[PDB]
Image (cartoon, rainbow, N blue to C red):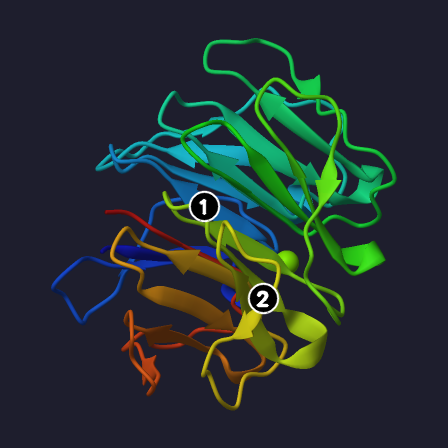
Amino acid sequence: GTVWVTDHGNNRVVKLAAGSNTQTVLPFTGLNTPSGVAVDSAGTVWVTDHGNNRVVKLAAGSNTQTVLPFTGLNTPSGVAVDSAGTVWVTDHGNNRVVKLAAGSNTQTVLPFTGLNTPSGVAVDSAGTVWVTDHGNNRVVKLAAGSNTQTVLPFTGLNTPSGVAVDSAGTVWVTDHGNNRVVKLAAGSNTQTVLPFTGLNTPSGVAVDSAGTVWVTDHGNNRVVKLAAGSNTQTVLPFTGLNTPSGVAVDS
Ligand SMILES: [Mg+2]
């Protein structure tokens, strides 16, 4: 239930530990316009350091930032990590999605086709990869071991900015251009719209195993949350956010 946020406008990553209402600032260094964040159950944090065309990670309680050995990134927009430690990145400026398997020294390009300005990525424990294909107003997926993408049956998306998936295969998307969050359950082809209100250019979404949903409400400099079944959003007690770009939660 810990929440991490890329506080883009302030070139920093903040967190609110489970049970705390006072954020901490993580000791990343030299970030610029950081665009997204991913975490694992060990509390390692990965960040797309967008303005520096790189991906960095920080282990829990450390003072060591590691630059991951990706190649040729341009304006990278989002990151996802699985329990095996593979890292996926939406390489926005190159219209592609790349990954580093844990322990690999060079990235792989995923066999998506026709992407434009991809904005975000999520993975599940089966290794399925979902991408917000922002420039085409759609969400695409590759199943583990497949090289044939499919397009999810969302409707009416505009400049979608981020995606999250749970262990049941439900998919949530920040439909940025429409100021809303939409979801599709696994066996569903009819989206619902979550009861957030007053969102402005929402930038990212995270879910936990209990079905709580957190959203970086970028245009209002805040993070909002709906617990599973809730109909009233809660503004988290972060302070000083500016143009926040992404959010990740752990269990
Ligand atoms: Mg973004």
Query: Residue beneath label 2, please?
Result: 174
- Residue 218 drawn at (x, y percent): 55, 74
Q: Look at label 1 and name its amino acid.
A: Gly
The label on residue 242 is none
Q: Is residue 243 visible?
A: no
Taking the spot 21% from the left edge, 37% from the top edge, the residue there is: 61
Is residue 20 placed above or below 25 in the rendered structure?
Answer: below
The label on residue 169 is 1
Kindly state the secondary structure of the residue where label 2 is placed: strand
Taking the spot 65% from the left edge, 48% from the top edge, the residue there is: 77
Q: Nearer the viewer, residue 5 or 64?
A: 5
- Residue 19 drawn at (x, y percent): 11, 63
Q: Nearer the viewer, mark 1 or mark 2?
A: 1
Q: Is 62 on the left or on the right of 135, as rendered?
A: left
Q: Is 246 on the left or on the right of 236, as rendered?
A: right
Q: Earlier in the sequence, mark 1 or mark 2?
A: 1
- Residue 86 drawn at (x, y percent): 48, 23
